[PDB]
Length: 63
Length: 63
Length: 177
Length: 83
Image (cartoon, rainbow over all chains, first blue to last red; front, side, top):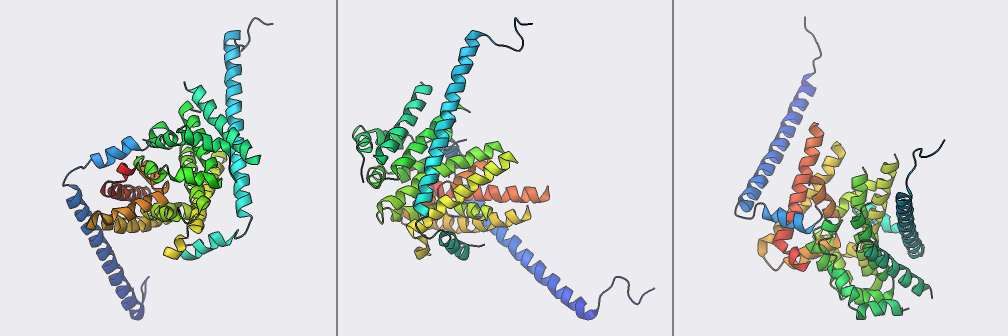
């Protein structure tokens, strides 16, 4: 068989390839930014007062 | 019939009466406070700028 | 006592309410001389711990009273001097269970909203800090609004959303951008 | 459920920018942080109390980040001392 079976055309094939590459780039950038932010927060919070920062509020505010 | 059918005793009857009166008083006070606040807001907002106050935000903030 | 303090708190609301109908009032003035407004604003701290239940209904009358004093022009003077902005910050407060949660936020928002728009440009400086320091939270409420328990919950959102909106237009946060 | 998740994503982004800014310089920016929490009080209280299938976990995750975002500003700004 052949000549077309749930297939696409080259003009649409290249467009789909470019769209997929762009989406993958955006997703990778977002994931890297999120990971960098998480690492920064972990480095800044691991110094001290890990649970006290929330305990003070749980004691002040309504539990 | 008689001598008791899903009934209560006087010692509990008076307590239930007092509890009902207290609950009704609290509910009436809350409702009156809410009505007074609503009337105050209606009197203060009916002056002018009834829809603009929200339109400015809908235009500034994300709809 | 649990019932005496509740009835006494609600009683003060009727006194100040009926007195205004009779721009000043001698009842509100007496409360300041007796150091009642001072200790009252101090109790606002740790409100989360206090908040059908007897403690819940008691707090309702407490915040309800403060809301009335912020409606008269003279109340802004005595109320503002109590430094209520710093009292509500230490507490960290900022289907039926959720409805009660918004009921507390509305009560606090109304007291602050009416207070800023009471005196004039002397309190707008504080309102901007409250919205800027707690930005984002109000944005979620203003966008949410834009069976019995459901309607009751949504009703609080409408009041809560409209509460902050009044403070914005009254404080002039749009000019700050 | 997906629409709400995107809403919190915006609030988190803004909260992080403001949270990190106040705790960056020092006591010169704490005066502004207190006004932001006092002027927008109540809204943050709802988030800090909420945290205390795929789309559900994603939505709750943003609440945890959003709730912890303001908490960092509080301890860094010193709003507890103001009471």
